[PDB]
Length: 49
Length: 29
Length: 96
Length: 96
Image 1 (cartoon, each protein chain N blue to C red):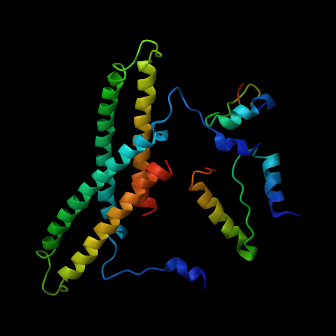
Image 2: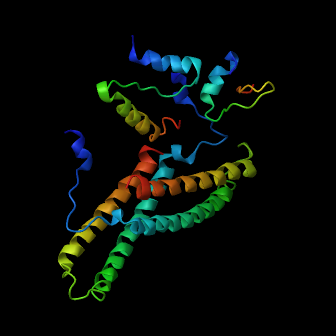
Image 3: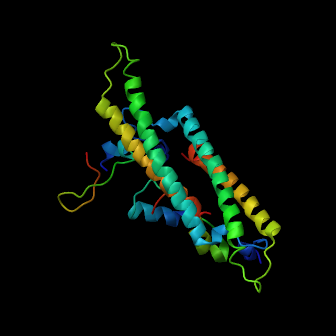
């Protein structure tokens, strides 16, 4: 029931990684906020892909 | 990575996966 | 043990110079000097470009407020200098 | 209308120089030159500091692999230079 369990399963089946994970809840506009979050995270050396 | 290596791989910021003999990407020992 | 990788590091035989605050000290005020000299080199360049567009200005072109144009331009060299400071301050104290 | 503030700007009478790609061009390869000269100035400094710790080394102290120590040190000046490049490239093309 957690928003980030989806995210987790992605990491437990495909890309096994010690990468950052920041999962957002921006209601209707979530998908974009996610782009932001991902964007910023990448522009801070936190991750490249 | 095989389990025994994990701590090392996690800490060597340059450890990277090499192609292997079956075609599988592994961290090398 | 994901969180273990916040201690990921492969140091050679010798520690990075950057861990030494003095090394960063040098390099910092190195760029601080390197910066103060640009600050003037740019002031010069604006002086030239000032009368350099006085000579090209036709009489149907708007009268250039030398006070206006040279104000915004100096203030800018100021900001831009200050900016450049904090930014070298960034790459040597914060995010090195 | 929150999203309206991604268009907030108070420009004076004259546009910021930075909106002109050429201005950034200048300043960029300005620091690129300013950078290449540091790159050497630092090579010099390492040469000195090399034999400068040969003269202070006691015989009970570990033998300093000049090849080792000078390798890591040159490679570093390289990285650090490269870094400094992208970083001025950052403040003039990306995040200005």
